[PDB]
Structures are given as C-alpha cells and as structure tokens.
Image (cartoon, rainbow, N blue to C red):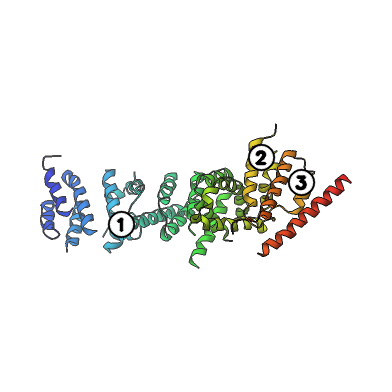
Amino acid sequence: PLPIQTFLWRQTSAFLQYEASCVSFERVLVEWELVQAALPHVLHCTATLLSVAETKLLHTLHWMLLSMATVELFVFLFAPLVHRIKLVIWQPMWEHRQPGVSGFTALVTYFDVAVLRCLLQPHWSEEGTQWSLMYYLQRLRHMLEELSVVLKAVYLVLNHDISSRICDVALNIVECLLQLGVVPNHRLALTMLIKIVKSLLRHQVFRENAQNCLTKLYKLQFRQTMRDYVNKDSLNNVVDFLHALLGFNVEGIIVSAMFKSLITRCASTTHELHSPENLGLYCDIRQLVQFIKEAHGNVFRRVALSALLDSVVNLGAIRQGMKRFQFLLNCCEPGTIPDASILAAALDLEAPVVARAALFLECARFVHRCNRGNWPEWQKLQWNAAKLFYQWGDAIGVRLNELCH
C-alpha cells in the first residue's frame, strides 16, 4: 500500500461519467502486486456499470486476469451477470462449469469455497442463486459420475423464501445428494424435504420424486424429529404440509406420529381459533381430521381415547387426553366421534374408573349442549345425530341389562 490509494477511490466515485471515465480507467491500468491491489476497484465498478463501455471494461478485466476475499467479491458481483453478458470464463460459466482462469481454478477449490461462503448471504440477488445452485447440481453430478456444509447452506437459504425455480432446483440437488449418500445431519435433510414439499402436469412429476426421496430417506429418530417439528413450526405451515401430502407407508407413519401432537398443540388456541379472520384455516383442519377418520387412521381412536389409554393416577396425562377429546368432539359430525361400541364396552375396560366416568359425563355435557341449541358454530345432520344418540342409548342399556341382570 502507498499514499496513491485515494486515486483508486476516485475511480469508484465516477461509477458509484459513463463514457468519459472509461478512457482514463483503461489508460492508467494499461500504461503484478499493483494489479492485484487494484483488481477489487475494477471488479466493483464494472459490475456496477454493467448492472460501448462494456467492451472496454471487459478488455480491462481480461488484461487484469491474464486471496479468498477477491474470489468472494468476484462471485458476489458476477454471479447474477452470467445470463446478461451473452470468453474463457463466460462461456464455461454459462453452463455452470468452473471458469478456465488458472488464478483460482487450481486445486489445493477456491471458487467452490468462495461460492459456498458467499451463498450464506440472506438476500443474494435471485438470479445469482439459480446459477450457484445449478453449479452445485452439476458438481454433484460429476461426483456421482466417478459435503454436509452444502446441505447446511442450502437449508439456510431455503427458509428465507421459495419459488418454483428455486424449489425445483433445490429438490433436484437434494435428490442428487441423497443418491450420493451424504446422509449416513438427518434432521437438516428432513427439514429441507419438508420445506421443499410444503409448496407443491408439471408439478406432479416432481411431487412423485419428492415422496420417492422421502421413502428413500425413511430407511434410515425420524419420528422424534418429526414430532419436534410439528410442535415447533407454526400451524399454517403444518396444515399446508398435510394438505400437500394427502390432498383430501409414509403417510401412515407420519400421521400416526404427528396427529397426537398436532391435536395437543392446537387444542390450547381456542381464543385465536374463534376469531373470524382465521376461520378458513379451521375448515382445512376439519377435512384433515375427517380424512384421518374416513379410512386412514385407526390411530384416531387411540388418540381420541388417549385419556384412558395412558394409564396414584396421573392427573396431568388424563387432563391432556381430555383436552384433546374436547377439541376432537367439538370439531365435526356431532355424536359421531365415539361409536356406540366403544361407549358400550367402556364399562368393563381395565382402566381407571375416573377416566371412564369423565368420558361419560363429557358425552353427557355434549348432549346437553346439543339440546340447548348451540351445536358447533355453523339441517339433516341434526336428524342424523338423533339416530346416533339412540344407538348409543340402546347399546348402553343392553350392556347394563346384561351386566346387572
């Protein structure tokens, strides 16, 4: 470094005129340590101007080219410019291959580490991202033709925002890494898969690939991490995930592992739930639970009767089970959640008497509310519930007669 540095800054002050500046800009450089020291200004200003001078700046850069921070700056400013320049570096770079300059193409990888480190930026211009991701895809393919930090970077960039192009390229690269066998980390990969599938003729093919990757990953903790994710992440995303997965085996295990915690967490939100703005969301959940009951979830019975399956008596567990039962019963099809058989058989089940009595009195209160007039806040279903109630009563009476008599 020498007192001349101010002159260099002056050049930036011209770019940060369009025609006049290029004359002296080319002259002073045309007329190795000084070249290296001056390269950052030239890279910055040419990137700024590009975002007849084009040819002059390109020639200046080529003359300059013919340490990690330098490549870092190079990538940050020139990655989005690839598609617009339309040669040793540009032509290979159009196909997402390493540039041919020997300055940093050499192997100790400088370009790779540069792109990886700078890609962590939260608001990189999207144009560059699409390139960088494709580059990684290509490199991974080359690896398969003849890395956890890459997964970490992809995960850190995915959360900020997702798009059709971004999600497609992310799915492709994640599939390529799974094919490579990077996973022996598991939590990150599963979370990335969740994020990718959360936003999905064109879409189905990738979706089929999505569940294929999910099945491949299933072979190797899954339940624990999923149970953590469902509670940690906001409901809207969880319900969107379930809608995408099902649409209204992997589905069996995921539901059997997640439904209990989903109901548990959603139960303690009634005040937010009733607010009209979010009412639409509730509708989705209804379908979800209905589907779980329709033909899929036998776990529904076990989750519904949790209060007496997880059993001095444990007050907290039974209270949580009853909270879940309250949410489920008041959710859909009044008088349909507990069938006649379960109520009739509840007398003899080898479970704490308190739980059975609580279930009976809760059904009693539900029937009382139905009588008073206030069904769930929304008919033929009114008449149907009468038949279900009569079946309940007949079964209970038959059981009582058989037992006592």
Residue designated by label 2: 318
Residue 192 position in % (x across, y down): 48, 50
Q: Secondary structure at mark 2?
A: helix
Residue 201 position in % (x across, y down): 50, 68
- Lower position in the chain sequence, tag 2 or tag 1: 1
Q: Amino acid type of disc 3?
A: Ala
Q: Residue at x 38, y 55 (%)?
A: 135
Outermost residue, top side = 312
Q: Which mark is residue 346?
A: 3
In contact (CB < 8 Å): disc 2 and disc 1:
no
- Lower position in the chain sequence, tag 3 or tag 1: 1
Q: Secondary structure at mark 3?
A: loop
Q: Is residue 65 visible?
A: no
Residue designated by label 1: 80
Circle 1 Cα neighbour tier, 10 Å, few/some/many (<14 / 14–19 / ≥20): many
Find the distance from the CA under tag 3 to the CA under tag 1: 67 Å
Which of 50/25 is in front? 50
Residue 364 position in % (x across, y down): 71, 48
Q: Amino acid type of disc 1?
A: Pro
Q: Secondary structure at mark 1?
A: loop
Which of 177/84 is in front? 84
